[PDB]
Each structure stands twice: as structure tokens, then as C-alpha cells.
Length: 49
DNA sequence: AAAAAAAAAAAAAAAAAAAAAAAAAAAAAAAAAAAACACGTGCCTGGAGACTAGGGAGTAATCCCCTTGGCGGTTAAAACGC
Image 1 (spheres, chains in turn brown, orange):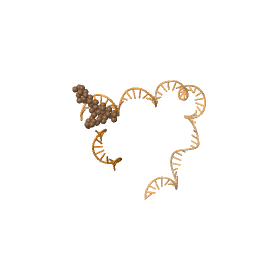
Image 2 (cartoon, chains in turn purple, cyan; image 1 turned 135 degrees about the vertical axis):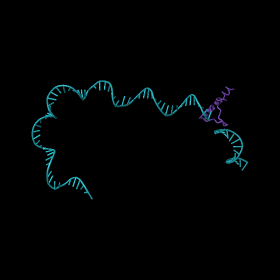
Image 3 (cartoon, chains in turn cyan, orange; image 1 turned 90 degrees about the vertical axis):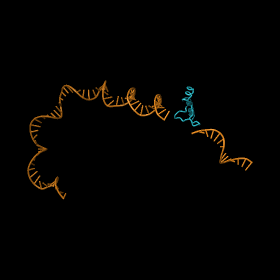
Image 4 (cartoon, helix red, strand yellow; image 1 turned 180 degrees about the horizontal axis):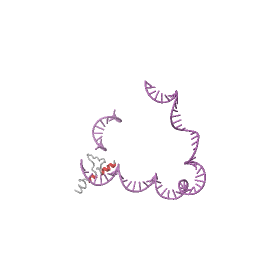
């Protein structure tokens, strides 16, 4: 479970790995979700601020 | 009048299609080491050549013994039938 919490802190988009459960019925938004994506920290905040 | 048990309110907690790259399994040919009937080699014991001389087999004559051939008399053996 410690490895599960560490992995979901790092990457919650890993297939074959149980998704982290948030309080509002959503998956947890990890740091990879903050960076990778069109609306991410790179494309939506550094590329397109 | 004081102690114990059940009921209810409050608080904490788990619950979509497409394409490139890599890993992997079945297969498959190529190439490098241990066996094994017959070939390579040297030795020798047996195969081969020559002379002697003799004794066992072939050849000639004879005969008589053994083998073959015929003719007749019941006749037991064979054949035929029910």
C-alpha cells in the first residue's frame, strides 16, 4: 500500500494498476497529469501563458 | 438515594480507432565435438614349389553266383454290394 500511494503520487495513469480514489468520484490528478496534456503546465502554462 | 444497562446523537473512515516500438515464443539452419565397420600397416605362420617313392586305384581276364524270366495250382487276398 505504501508503494501504491507512492505510485499514485507519481503516476495515476498506469494501466494494470488500481486507480486512486478521490472524494468526489474522480481519479487523482498526479504530477504527470499536471505536466503532460494540452492544458498542462508545459503546453497550457509555459507554452501558452 | 446510588449503580448498571440500553437507546440515540456525534465523530472518524473507505468507497474509441490507429500506428510505431519492444518483448517473446516456435522454428530452423549452420557449425563444432564423441562413436565405428573397414581401411592402412607390419609381422609371421601358413601357403606354395620341387623331388622322391610308394602304395592305392585303374585296367585286363574269368566265373559263378546271383539275379531275372516264364508256367502252372489252389487260393487267401482283394473287390463288390447291402
